Amino acid sequence: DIQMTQTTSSLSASLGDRVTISCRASQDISNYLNWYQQKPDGTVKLLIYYTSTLHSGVPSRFSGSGSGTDYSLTISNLEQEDVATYFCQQGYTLPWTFGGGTKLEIKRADAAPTVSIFPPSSEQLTSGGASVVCFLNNFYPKDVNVKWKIDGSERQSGVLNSWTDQDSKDSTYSMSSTLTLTKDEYERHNSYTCEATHKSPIVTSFNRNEC
Amino acid sequence: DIQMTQTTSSLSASLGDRVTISCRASQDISNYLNWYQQKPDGTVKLLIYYTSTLHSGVPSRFSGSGSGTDYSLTISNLEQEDVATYFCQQGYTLPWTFGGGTKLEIKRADAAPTVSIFPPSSEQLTSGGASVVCFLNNFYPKDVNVKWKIDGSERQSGVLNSWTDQDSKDSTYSMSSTLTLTKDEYERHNSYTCEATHKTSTSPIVTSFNRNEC
Amino acid sequence: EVQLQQSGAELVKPGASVKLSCTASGFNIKETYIHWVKQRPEQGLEWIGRIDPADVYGRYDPKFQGKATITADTSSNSAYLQVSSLTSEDTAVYYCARSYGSSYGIDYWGQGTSVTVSSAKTTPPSVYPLAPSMVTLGCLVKGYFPEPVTVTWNSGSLSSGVHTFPAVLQSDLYTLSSSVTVPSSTWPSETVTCNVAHPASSTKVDKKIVPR
Amino acid sequence: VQLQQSGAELVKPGASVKLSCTASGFNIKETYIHWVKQRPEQGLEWIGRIDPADVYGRYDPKFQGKATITADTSSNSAYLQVSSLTSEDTAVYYCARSYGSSYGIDYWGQGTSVTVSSAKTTPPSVYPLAPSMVTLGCLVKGYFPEPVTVTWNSGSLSSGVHTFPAVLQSDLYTLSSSVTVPSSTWPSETVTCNVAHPASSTKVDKKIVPRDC
Amino acid sequence: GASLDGRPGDRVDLSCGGVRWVWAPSFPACKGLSKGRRPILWAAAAGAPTVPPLQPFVGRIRRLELLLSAGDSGTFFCKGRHEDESRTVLHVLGDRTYC
Amino acid sequence: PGASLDGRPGDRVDLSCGGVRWVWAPSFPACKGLSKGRRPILWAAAAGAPTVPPLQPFVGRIRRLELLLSAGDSGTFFCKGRHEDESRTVLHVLGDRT
Ligand SMILES: *[C@@H]1O[C@H](CO[C@]2(C(=O)O)C[C@H](O)[C@@H](NC(C)=O)[C@H]([C@H](O)[C@H](O)CO)O2)[C@H](O)[C@H](O[C@@H]2O[C@H](CO)[C@H](O)[C@H](O)[C@H]2O)[C@H]1NC(C)=O
Ligand SMILES: *[C@@H]1O[C@H](CO[C@]2(C(=O)O)C[C@H](O)[C@@H](NC(C)=O)[C@H]([C@H](O)[C@H](O)CO)O2)[C@H](O)[C@H](O[C@@H]2O[C@H](CO)[C@H](O)[C@H](O)[C@H]2O)[C@H]1NC(C)=O
């Protein structure tokens, strides 16, 4: 229908700055566009309705400006709590369209990760399987290209990673990598280790030690 | 273009009787129908506007009736000044339409004509022409067959008649018949008659003129 | 004083155009609608059309298909009927009448204006006297063109006994005779004069009926 | 004045699901009920709206016929009836309230997760992960469907928790969690990774013990 | 059809042949008005003009009384059900063309 | 293209026409409604003393006007040009029935 476009799909910004989210419409929507906030796994909040007008209980730092066809939401003071995706939407014609959205990340000092490697538990080893877990508890920015070696050999197969969202508590990122192998394969190889490269590389170790 | 038809085009009526002129319309006229009286060669008067309504100075004897499509004009205690034609007229839509008319004749006793034949004057005769005139006066009813037997022999050629309308005096018609001949023809034959065929008496009314010159 | 002054009778050649007049006495034409009516010789009335003098455009019957164009002049307090491309089917009397509207009709009617459509020429009459206790005597009116002829007797004083018969057309010439019935004591004792007047040819002939 | 969304549904492909949304405090007869579809890690999609008095709700043509929103005023609740389900339907379904065009979708429901999979419900297999400060883990492998509520030492250990999102290899889910406690508190104190799978009615508790042989 | 002509200060009763209708005229004038058919009276439970025109009553198809004034010149329609019209032409004597 | 709206009684929404001597003319859902089709309410105002919309005397202004909504106001609103052209704004008022 009236396809809604948001120029940028991600916007990183440091605390105490002003930012703008732009929304262009397929046709003049005579100011019948509202703005929405969706917090990570939190509820969806209506921020601004009918372009300019603030919604009840929404802070004043949120400003809804808009031309006839070009609409732009602006967060004047940057707060940690504002880490959320913002969406525009038209109500002018009946198939109401929700735009692409713009995730708002927080810019902060570059933190080095807290790399910890964990050996497969003697619980999982009974289930005819093995899993190596390597974490990077507290770091920034988002991208970190992990590479782990078992006796030096490169293992790219069966590697599955997972990233958390930027917390509105300390404004940091965290990553979990899981190397899943069959019981026999993990029993054949010894001295498993995980290394990490982030903008000397941080190298962690977990040798096959008796206990 | 809505049409108007009067059921009758001529109505003979005795003095002081009650008469009606009916009018049928092609559409619903919604009382927008007026009546007119046009006297012989006299002015045409507006009798009764918007059906039953009468025009200022029009006598009470005149009454207007009807609704929808058939409207009527009614005249009581008839007078010798009511001998005129009456017209229906719609005004409901813009091609204003008049009815055909109904001439109102006044009935009377059977009157025999006063038949008078006149020879061509010695004035006309110099102009190389001759005309015989026969005036039939004060008669009732309207139809009367004229007959011009030149020396008894039937003459159907060059005969031209003229009638006057119902008179106001004794309400009787008069007729005039003219037999026009060329100087020579009139000078050729002697006897010139003029016979009226009217139903007043048992016999036809016969008048004559024989030219005398030697 | 509610008078509608109609123009004098006209003799027109066929195919030509005539513009008839109608003048308003006393009343202002701005206050009524003007209506014109046709009347074929010895026939019914035919509504030609009407006009609001405040407007230029008159509304007429479709039978008078662009021929008749009524146009009134407020300034001169008079209306006009212009009828173009004439025929013998147009030889009639034309009435001018004032109306206040649908629910009032044509209240004041004009005297009429006679229009004769003929290629024939104006011709004065040739009066002929017709001589023969009561007696009848008349006078002949042969070959006059066009109508009318005001026929009176002994300078109009002899009203009682008069019978004026209507005109007869014959090869484009008219013929009418009139008869008077006077007592046999008054004739040949008194003078009897058949007074004829032809307005069209501006003649007024008077012929004394003398015993032959 | 809240919007009560029904519990998350696991549906077989091609079948039909009728979701629920109940109005608290307010009367539904006093607003338009709107529904929204949110594909995993994707934008929102407006399904359609309804005037509860009408009970013949308008829908987006891309969804026309597939989804049928019908509300019950008597029970003060609305329903989303979705049929002929695909993997492209595995998403969260929000029920929101709106006062009109000039006001937008103001109150938003929590959202109902619809998982379209021919795969069966499987409880998790919790694996403890023992090694200045001390980082400790807990692995939750092989569960179906999502979600799993993971807490530390009966949720009393809020500070230092890090719960990573679930990973599907092949209709199998895996998520790990990490807690950072001081080297003084461990192995001195008990540390229990509390895992809760509502879908399978399980609540498993694995104490992290220092690894030996 | 019906084609009428009157004077200002007169009154003309006008009706229809309708199938519960609406009278809707257009006038060749603009005394504060504009081009196009403007409905002036409609049926309800007891028909009345209300605020645009204030000279027509109702006899109580439907019949109305109209006080002509100056500028009521126009075609009066009597639009019924499914284009069941009933037009009436009206012309008042006079041309008010001064600004 | 097209404009489809939804409001509730006591609200007020703006209606217009990009395609411009005109005339606004809407039709409202017949059930519990006296008239059964498209009906004119406003015509472009001339250089005199003009105002008043027939079936709803609560529309303020140019024919780019605001409308206060109430019972039965649900229906499509057409703005009309000199020939053929029409700009329609569909409208729905909350809880429209008996
Ligand atoms: C305009 O029409 C009215 C009729 O309006 C009414 C009615 O009684 O039918 C008045 C109500 O206020 C109105 N209600 C609202 C709020 O719209 C109802 C209507 O029934 C509802 O809309 C639906 O149920 O409509 C009058 O006929 C009025 O004419 C005048 O009536 C007077 C009566 O004493 C008097 O005779 C006046 O001379 C006459 O003009 C008319 N308005 C005007 C100013 O003429
Ligand atoms: C309809 O009328 C308005 C004027 O309305 C008012 C006024 O003067 O504000 C409203 C008042 O309540 C009313 N009553 C009183 C007691 O004041 C008066 C009343 O008519 C006078 O007192 C009587 O003399 O009238 C406008 O004329 C409006 O026209 C539109 O105005 C626009 C302004 O931005 C714009 O210029 C438009 O072109 C123009 O049409 C008119 N409404 C419509 C939709 O035509």
Image (cartoon, coloured by chain):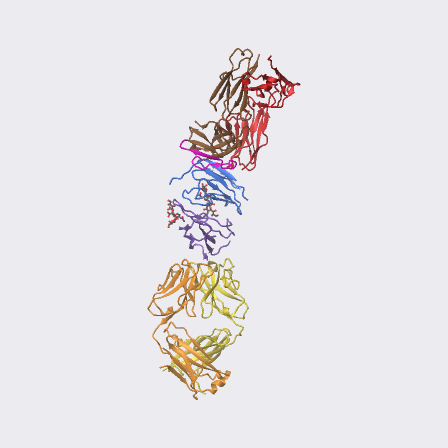
Chain colours: A orange, B red, C brown, D yellow, E blue, F purple
Q: Judge by depth and name the residue closer to the eye, E3 or B126.
A: B126
Work out whether residue F19 can be spotted.
yes
Q: Residue furthest left?
A: A16
Work out whether residue D27 can be spotted.
no
Residue C60 among magenta residues = yes
Q: Residue furthest bottom?
A: A210
Q: Is residue D131 above or below residue C130?
A: below
Tell me which segment is drawn in magenta: C52-76
**Image quarter for residue B157?**
top right
Q: Residue at x 49, y 50 (%)?
A: F38
* Quarter occupied by the N terminus of chain C: top left
Name the chief secondary structure element in magenta: loop
Q: Residue furthest right?
A: B202
* Quarter occupied by the C terminus of chain C: top right
Residue A190 among magenta residues = no
Estimate the x, y position of residue C18 in percent, counting from the top left. 47, 31
Estimate the x, y position of residue D138 in percent, counting from the top left. 44, 79
Q: Judge by depth and name the residue closer to the eye, D175 or A56.
A: D175
Q: Judge by depth and name the residue closer to the eye, D20 or D145.
A: D145
Q: Number of labelled discs?
A: 0
